[PDB]
Image (tube, rainbow over all chains, first blue to last red; front, side):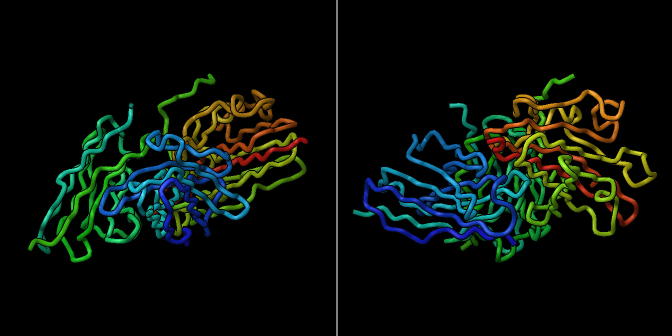
Length: 228
Length: 176
């Protein structure tokens, strides 16, 4: 199967530049988007940009104001993210991910920990922020888009210190291996993910993501934990 | 009529749920300077359907003629009853990857010096006649990737299902 392997954790001084590598093996390198997403400790997911390697030009979130350079070496099937002018707030796990012809990021690197040490955008609103529930109960998660995204909405599950796992894409399509107690619904601006009956493996943080248009945008997440 | 529908959006995988690493990927059948993707047998329903059949047209020399055969609905009973092709105005209109989705593009705006003959063997150069052709130019400066869809994955004959055909035309720089 497809494997994304990223370069190791790094400690960087303020003002330095870091260049993270993402080696792709299995499937096809040149014609599929390689995507960069970061997560500051205890915070949400933030899309940084993407490259389709044959194009020899990445696309970037305006937020990063040219601090981000995304490149690919087609001869080694390796993608790169460089972030310059590093500061405290850039301390994060940097994820590379790829699409596999279904538009969504469905294959993920392990992430690269980087510790820094001495306008038209679609807003996704996720609720509730937290859910504490017991085994066998029903969990519902809501995600509103600020503009129509048709059915271009994905749901990810994330366990502590692990890459996001795709559960649902095109609003209602289960990823291979996802159990039937998961279902997604909605179109336009209002979306829901439902877990009919909670199992121990279901406790996690969940994120919706629109992939209608760049920049890709995430809800702030729902932390679904066991009732005390 | 040549007009692009800016709203049209799809994906290589369509509704098959197959990721590109499980596509059956193969090279076009190349005889002199004619590169052929024939979907007549590849898309017939089988017990193992639906599969994605990805025909790779890899071009790094001049004046290559690309020919794509997509079997017509009813050409053989049962086998192609739910077949579809995208774009409808192939080969004047093609699909390119914009962000992570396929959207329509005028091929002549993508590639300078493209030959499309209005007719193939006295018939309209259009999938409604079962076959399209075009000839790429003597020089190409920038790597260019575009797609056609010949999708039989919704044809079901009891426990046999058709396959989704993709054409990926991957044009490297050449002519120097």
